[PDB]
Image 1 (tube, each protein chain N blue to C red):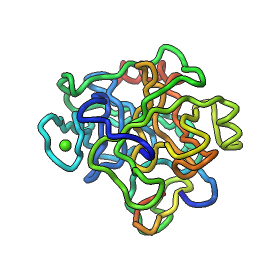
Image 2 (image 1 turned 30 degrees about the vertical axis):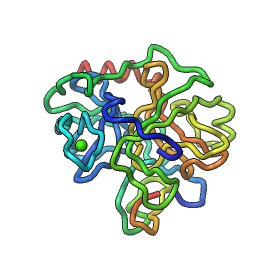
Image 3 (image 1 turned 180 degrees about the horizontal axis):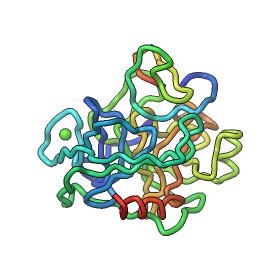
Length: 223
Length: 34
Ligand SMILES: [Ca+2]
């Protein structure tokens, strides 16, 4: 997260870290057994870390749970990033508490202008070495379809939206992928991609979660 | 990210060369994709 603020320990209780020997992506807990992340965050043998704040120090509220299943959307395209969503099943159920909690799925899509919370342990500079210990946060609005499509000619599919600031300065960045964009208490986005981080005219691009509610429910029901 | 305006996913990934990186991401001088 570039241009953001320190969240505060466990203030984003649905935020998880995906760890394969090091933190590489975020995710969002949607029930005691399932995490939503990005398809491009797929690895075999993922360990989900919940209740984390400082990912490099044991602080006492963490739960480490291995993924038993990591299910990429069947139509995910790794060049265009269309359908950039993945469901991870936990080997055992997380113990829900004030610091480890699920976030609701949307019942419809959010309109442009809606304010959201974006979070993660991604780079806190647009380039160079600035990977944080503690969770960082950003408030950012959903941008219009026309703004998004003009910023990224030919690159925006029906399954993507832009959020952030056309003036730049505030954005998600490398290490934030797969993490939450939450608006009015619903999980509306997944950190996906961008051209750089926090550059003018190049806002972050996010997976449109509202398009996948049926698929999420069906996958959870059959796995 | 590189300078070409391509699709660069925001994953944190260690790398030695561009082919280690997803999409249009390149391997930056610090050994991470961007
Ligand atoms: Ca910790």
